[PDB]
Image (cartoon, rainbow, N blue to C red; front, side, top):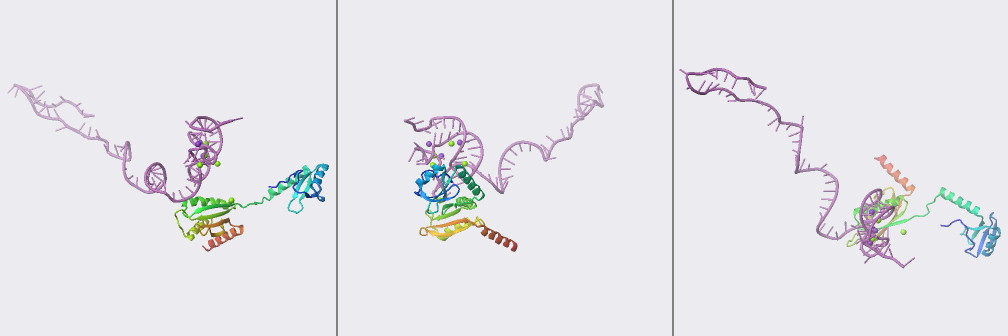
Amino acid sequence: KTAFSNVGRKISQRVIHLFDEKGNDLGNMHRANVIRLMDERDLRLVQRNTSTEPAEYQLMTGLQILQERQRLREMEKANPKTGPTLRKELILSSNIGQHDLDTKTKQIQQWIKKKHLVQITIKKGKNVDVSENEMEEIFHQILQTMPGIATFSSRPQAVQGGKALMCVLRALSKNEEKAYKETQETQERDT
RNA sequence: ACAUUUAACUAAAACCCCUACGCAUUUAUAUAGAGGAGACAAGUCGUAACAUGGUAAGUGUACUGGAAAGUGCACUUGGACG
Ligand SMILES: [K+]
Ligand SMILES: [K+]
Ligand SMILES: [K+]
Ligand SMILES: [Mg+2]
Ligand SMILES: [Mg+2]
Ligand SMILES: [Mg+2]
Ligand SMILES: [Mg+2]
Ligand SMILES: [Mg+2]
């Protein structure tokens, strides 16, 4: 995380683009001169933008730093963007039992309702040789439990020289979900 | 409930009842279906225990969880400890 707080007296860079407490642009200056300003005016230094090639810092009072920090947290509460997508993964075997596959299927379902990405790998079993098409059946069994709740993010693909298949499942987009409801309703009208 | 009559110059003859057992009660077997234990065997998913077993283990109790188990409270050492 990046916090809106006083950077301190030790500034990372040597050349610093500085602004005034009122926003007046003071231009670029050396960090040694900035520390002298912070002491002469009794002000603290915050980092407003780092993307700019010349590092941009602004002088601010403790009261201002508080108001901005309060402002920002009122925006994020109003607009809490879910930034990270978490890639959960399950390595399965071809000879997995039904009780174990039913347990791992329920686990996959809970990951999809949380809007995660589920990478499913299926590997050849111990003492067992299987047709690569048979391994692909498990993917369709897992997804069949989630008819209108999930779909192939990446379709089944052979990996490790064909020894083990791979896949990625995802939650259906809102548009794809309304389409499924529509198609399902049309079938209801037909029947 | 039943009630002793005839007979008696030797003495004997009459005497003969009916109510229970069932839709009760006792015990057991058979049968729809649902579970447990053990044996064989070692497939499936984890690695809970045994080493400080990789979060020391366990007792009681509570809650929770695919599963061993996890966590809380007290207790035990059948653990450790300048
Ligand atoms: K344990
Ligand atoms: K132990
Ligand atoms: K206990
Ligand atoms: Mg990861
Ligand atoms: Mg263990
Ligand atoms: Mg342990
Ligand atoms: Mg305990
Ligand atoms: Mg818990």
